[PDB]
Length: 66
Image (tube, rainbow, N blue to C red; front, top):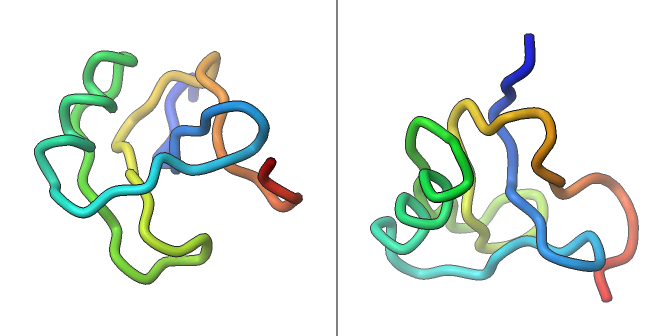
């Protein structure tokens, strides 16, 4: 469908660095997701992972963050 679990991105192909869960939940839900949390030690380091983020919101994909 139109939603996916994903790292929400900020320009240009960067995760939102994090430490605490509430920050990520706030960020993710503002952007239409159901919830979110801070994933420590993931594919791109520590970043906010959103649950059921709408597909029109950019996400982290393979490539260089800058």
